[PDB]
Length: 58
Length: 194
Image 1 (cartoon, rainbow over the protein chains, first blue to last red):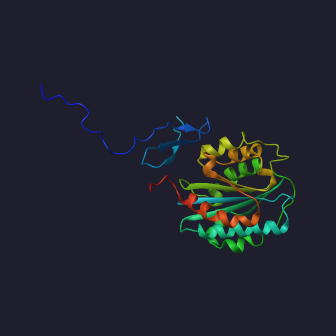
Image 2 (image 1 turned 180 degrees about the horizontal axis):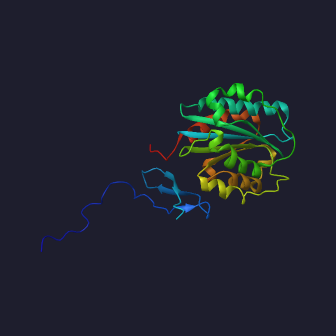
Image 3 (image 1 turned 45 degrees about the horizontal axis):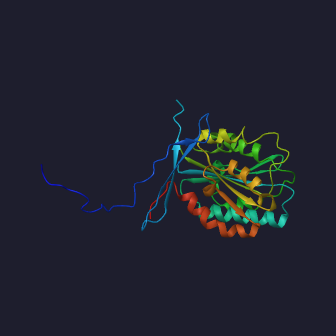
């Protein structure tokens, strides 16, 4: 073996990863789309992100 | 090339000439702080009929909003914001009217009352504007937008999310206070970081 390794220490980084939403269109017959992701945590503040998607119209 | 911003002001008979003045003060002041080197403006007034005051092609010749907004008079009538925005996407944002292709097109609507007497609905107009990629912002002014049932129509005129494209004001004078947020949210092409 190598060495028994239990919970030595927790990882830092952000309080969590970013939320990945799907591109929900506004119009079926081609239109704009939106996306929103939020980040929360103990010390991490409520970070909000709102992006815009585009329909391919294939 | 940069952006094509069109202003849609209501000319209904409910708005008094003194308040209609506050509206033209707003659009001209907003037009100035948003006057870029590749940004053109267009404005169409609506009630039951529609009157274009200036298109992007002529704003390029005369980039002074105060001289094109000053001679603007009221039309008087009811509200036809549905058929109005429809004409914007087809006429105001038309290439032959000075509208550029591949340029960011943003539309702002200022109304005081719920759509009454309009033969067209939002379902027959909005999905069209969404296709061409025209992003909208709406400003609610008056008692007509104090109820959440009326606010819904504002959320239909503007683009999602409503908490980003829907502004509400109690009086035409208080429009000066929303000029700041409008300017920032119209320049924000994407969600920046802190």
